[PDB]
Amino acid sequence: KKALKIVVVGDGAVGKTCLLLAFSKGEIPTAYVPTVFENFSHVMKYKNEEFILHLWDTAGQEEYDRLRPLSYADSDVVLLCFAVNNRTSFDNISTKWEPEIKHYIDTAKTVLVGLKVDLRKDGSDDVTKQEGDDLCQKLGCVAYIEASSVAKIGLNEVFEKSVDCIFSNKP
Ligand SMILES: Nc1nc2c(ncn2[C@@H]2O[C@H](COP(=O)(O)OP(=O)(O)OP(O)(O)=S)[C@@H](O)[C@H]2O)c(=O)[nH]1
Ligand SMILES: [Mg+2]
């Protein structure tokens, strides 16, 4: 079985837990509960095979900074998550998240994921697709993908690209 460990990191409340649950279960939590950590195992049928995804959920809050590195060992892919309506979370990718990840698991491939894309509107300085593409280039991510756990947009694409960058026949 082709398996991989995918870890999700990013500011508090960007939508990390909802991403994993909307992807793997097809529905999100009715009540928002901040994560300490959580590990899921999910079978995804893709390209005529079944892949075992070990999904590692982490705490976006800095109160848990000391604990989070405990989740990074042997990570195949890291999802650098921000919410497109929270520019601070976007900026924090470059200053906090990508560096933290490159410190503890520099061998993992990174995927930039712009969450809550359902909330994006002109005239509020939301993170645009171009900005995400620019950052993906700057940080050397495999891709920038936009998603909404609520509207069910881009969910499979996040995890298909995660599988691809590890097991595919091409970049
Ligand atoms: N509109 C919209 N709201 C979302 C979306 N994803 C998550 N949310 C909401 O944002 C809030 C935080 O989502 P959640 O997934 O729990 O954040 P988190 O990144 O896991 O937060 P933490 O555990 O590190 S504190 C919740 O109220 C959730 O319903 C989305 O795609 N669109
Ligand atoms: Mg969470």
Image (spheres, rainbow, N blue to C red):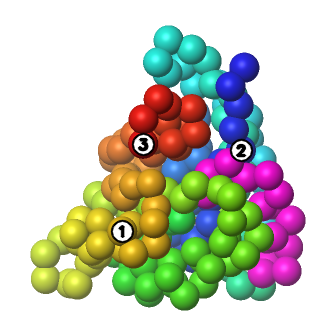
Which residue is the site of mark 1?
A: 137
Which residue is the site of mark 3?
A: 171
Of residues 53 and 166, which is closer to you in this image? 166
Q: Does residue 22 appear in this view?
A: no
Between disc 1 and disc 2, whose residue precedes?
A: 2
Q: Is residue 4 above or below residue 35?
A: above
Q: CA distance from mark 1 to mark 2?
A: 23 Å
Q: Amino acid at mark 1?
A: Gln
The C terminus sits in image quarter: top left
Residue 149 placed where, x, y %? Answer: 43, 49
Q: Amino acid at mark 2?
A: Lys
Of residues 111 and 122, which is closer to you in this image? 111
Q: Residue shown at 68%/25% (left/top)?
A: 2
Q: CA distance from mark 3 to mark 1?
A: 14 Å
Q: Is residue 88 above or below residue 79?
A: below
Which residue is the site of mark 2?
A: 5
